[PDB]
Amino acid sequence: AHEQVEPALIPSNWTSVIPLLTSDFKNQYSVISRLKNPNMKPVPYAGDIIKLMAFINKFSSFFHSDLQNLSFQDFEVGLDLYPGDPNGSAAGIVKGPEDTSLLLYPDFMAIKDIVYCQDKMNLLFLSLLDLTFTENFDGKSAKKKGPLTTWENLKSSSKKVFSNPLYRLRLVAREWGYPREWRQQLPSDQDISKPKTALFEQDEQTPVVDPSHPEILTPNIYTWNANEPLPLESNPLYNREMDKNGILALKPMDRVVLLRALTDWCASHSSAIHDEIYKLTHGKKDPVFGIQTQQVPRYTIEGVDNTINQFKKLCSLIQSRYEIRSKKKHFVKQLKEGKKPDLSRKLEILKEIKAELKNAVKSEKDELLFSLYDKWVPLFEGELPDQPLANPFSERLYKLRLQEFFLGRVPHIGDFYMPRLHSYGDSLEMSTFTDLRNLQALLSKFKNNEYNAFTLFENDGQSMSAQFKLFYHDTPSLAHDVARGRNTSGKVYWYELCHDSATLLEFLEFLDYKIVKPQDEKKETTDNNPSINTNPLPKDAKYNTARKKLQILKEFLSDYYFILRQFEQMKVQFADMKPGKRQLRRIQRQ
Amino acid sequence: KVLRDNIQGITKPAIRRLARRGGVKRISGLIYEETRGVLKVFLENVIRDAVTYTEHAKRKTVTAMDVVYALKRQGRTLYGFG
Amino acid sequence: KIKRVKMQQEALRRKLSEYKNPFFDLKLKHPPSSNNKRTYSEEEDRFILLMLFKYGLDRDDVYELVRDEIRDCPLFELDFYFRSRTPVELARRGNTLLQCLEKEFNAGIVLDDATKDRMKKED
Amino acid sequence: QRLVREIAQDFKTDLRFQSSAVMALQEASEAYLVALFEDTNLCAIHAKRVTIMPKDIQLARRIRGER
């Protein structure tokens, strides 16, 4: 209008790299496990592990470096959990096509490694006990610096380090609250929390001796039906072995439960971290778009292709906006007295690049964004402080609320989870968690495999979690249950997709079927589908954008596959800290 | 089935028994772990090469001859075992 | 103060009986916020008030109880801020929103709160 | 015997053991240990004390020349 007025970069559409998920998208029924296939496994215990890991990631400064490269598999083998069972762990895993026996991890891999993992989980357990209870000297203590627990600390001569913390914990636990599975659940289906236990009100006080106040503040009161914990002997907490034995004295699932619990009260009471988190998240700033629990990067929710299309559209619009901004009457007349240095350097450099970019052609129009993102960041000062396409993993405001092993949201299905490792402070050298540009660049370096296993571990690959798995989460069904009455006490919403490269390609194969748009909508994606995997989605145009995201993630997974299998072999090559110099002399000798 | 952590099965009273039979009167508390590690080392070397004999023998049962051969090669020839 | 919860009992009776899918329908933008770093988003709080009132205004232990649900809610275990908030602080929030619906319904709570009739006067 | 089994786990799986072998293992062990401590006492006595300390142990081990 005035000077083709600066098109307002509305935060709603033009965020930082950080959108939200709002968790109410599937208000319509989407419960069908049509995505089921042979390469799906019921894992009742995963998301618990997930919270474990994400917590550990956000608290890197608190934790040992050996903790920093831990993986899902570490915990599986170390904690003795096998997938398959809707009821916990399918004890043992069958091997090959048929198996009368089951793999029985020790009978399946080198045992020192299993021992090694177990020691890690004992170490983390002890460390968590410390962080919960070494709080008498809160946060800063005589041994202030570093994680509170070390290898020698567990390998110390106390021989029963677990004793006193266990004592402290069984003291504070009864009042700190219990999980359902460690609650003495009601046999009496009458002392539901909602009603009460017994009728303490023998009778209502109808004949008030004070008729002047017929109102009664004691109409009908009861005895209270608080949930109870188990008996102490029925409390696995009261099993003496952990004092010396450590965490490996239980049923596996119970171990899981106690770990989740230890995380629970650590977050609720480890006053150092407990204040630290609130300092970090409830400082003097709110989300750029509005306060919300769960958020992801932009390309994670939309994909590289659509986000770069929309952000090229954004780039063109905002470049025109800047050109408007400089030669603007009030702006010009306030420029000569120099309002802001950014309002000077930005304007001059944006003019030079308008000259050099009107030279750039429309085919170069798309490329100029990705070539000039380096100089483009300093442009966004008066604009959003962070790019609509920026690095999420540099924000102390989008730090607590962030979930990262999310890998994709898909309509009528749910969400796709990729626990890979820590990406905060430490573990950034090849951290897969980064800005879309340099992320895809690193992917490029590993499709052409410029960097390999030796380079991979030379560049902090040992502090890089070696292995992985792949999971899908059914948000629609669980949210529907929650908003519809809590049918669950032990129902499952996590399923496994692929643990390794071979299964990775298997599932890529299987998912390309889903990405096949419903040509069966004009029928008359594979055969034998109503039996083992519902490849043909129900015939409609609902999945069009769903399949766009599906193709996008297929792309993502192909891109990942290179580096993922590269780690998969780097570990095999370089599991042990070894003077690989002689290993390279192997090649130079040949 | 797995095994672990019997290095603690070497008790302090046994340790100080050995020390006494060695003619030592007074002992640091730090000695025990030191000893356990050193013993770990010794035992590892000896078992290692003993096994080495075992496999090249294509057997699946460690024999006392393999054991004696190993410590004799080390330099502590043990008599009394053929 | 005891009565204060009584019509708050009444007040929340209204709303949880009032909306149809309050976990996706509810509105408290009459008192959006007094003076706050407005950390808990609405639908989070919709659950809790749904959970608080599905207990009801027990004025005894609910804040203890919902923590357990937050300890146990599959969707709500996912927040960590929901955990480093003990029922003590949960009061601060919970009362606030009690007050928020209170102030939203301050023209609607007393609509069925403070009138009692007697035998011999037409009302 | 259990320590024997644990350590030997590492190199090959599912090994069997002569009990006689177990014995031979031990005698070798304790004799070696004995020589170790007696030298350790030599260290301590030359060091003008009567309580043994690990530095003596390690220094003797340095002397004999096992690295």
Image: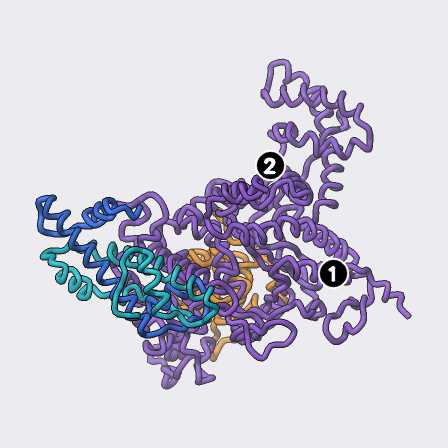
List x then y, in percent, for residue A44.
54, 70
- Residue with the mark numbered 1: A509
List x then y, in percent, for residue A123.
37, 57
User: Chain B drawn in what color?
Assistant: cyan
- Of residues A248 and D19, the one nearer the viewer is D19
List x then y, in percent, for residue A60.
44, 48
Q: Is residue A211 left or right of residue A142?
A: right
Q: Is residue A414 left or right of residue C60?
A: right
Label 1 packing within 10 angstroms: few (<14), some (14-19), many (20+): few
For the point 66% across and 57% down, which residue is it? A409
Q: Mark 1 belongs to which subunit?
A: A
The amino acid sitting under disc 2 is Asp
- Residue with the mark numbered 2: A386
Q: Is residue A401 above or below residue A78?
A: above
Label 2 packing within 10 angstroms: few (<14), some (14-19), many (20+): many
Name the secondary structure under disc 2.
loop
Residue A395 image label: none
Q: Residue furthest front?
A: B82
Q: Residue furthest right?
A: A524
User: Chain D drawn in what color?
Assistant: blue
User: Chain A drawn in what color?
Assistant: purple
User: Chain C drawn in what color?
Assistant: orange
For the point 34% across and 77% down, which residue is it? A210
| Residue A445 appears anywhere in the view | yes
Q: Mark 2 belongs to which subunit?
A: A
